[PDB]
Length: 207
Image (cartoon, rainbow, N blue to C red; front, side):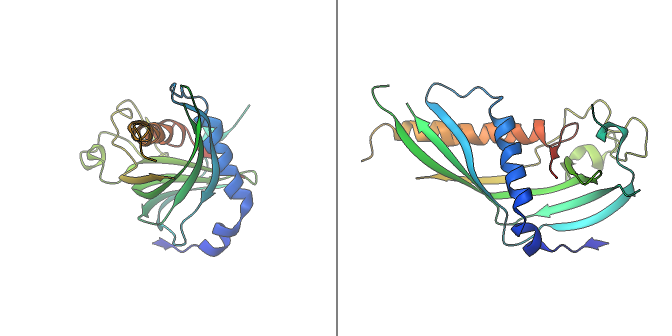
C-alpha cells in the first residue's frame, strides 16, 4: 500500500524548509549548552535528494489533541528512511579565545512508524516509534489512535527512532579535544530533541 511522493516538489518547497529550521532552533535553545559553546543555531536544513519509503497503514481523523488553544485527514505510516538528509549548523568555541565552527549532520536513518496530520492548512509529524521496537513485537503498546489507551504507559520505554547518524565539522592543538565533546554532545542532544520534541506526544508542526 505504498504512498508515492513528489520529492522534487517537497524538497523545493521553502515554506517547509524554513518551518523545520524554525522547529529545530526553537526547541534547540530550550537546552543547556555547556561552557565550551555559544551561538549554536541551524543555518540550513536540507532534505535528501531521495525520498523515504512511505507506506500507508491507516486512515483516521486527526486526534482531539491535535486541537489547540472534512477536509482534514490523518495517515499512520511506515517511514523507511535510509536517505541522504543533512542539517547544517553554526557554532562558537570557548577561554582566552573564540573560534567559529561549522557542522553537518548526515546519515539520518529511521525505520519508523509515524502519524501525519493535515488539518487547517497545516501539517503535523509525530513519530510513534521504530518499527523494530520490541514493544510492538510483544504488543504492550497500543499504536492505533482508534483506539483506547493509545500510547499508554510504557511509551517512555521506546527505543530510539534514530538508527544512525553522521556528524563532521569544518593547526591541530587540544581544541580537537573539544570538537569531539561537541560532536558527541550534539548527537546525544539531537537524539533527545527527536525523542522529546518530534516523537508523540510531541510533534513537528509545519504549514
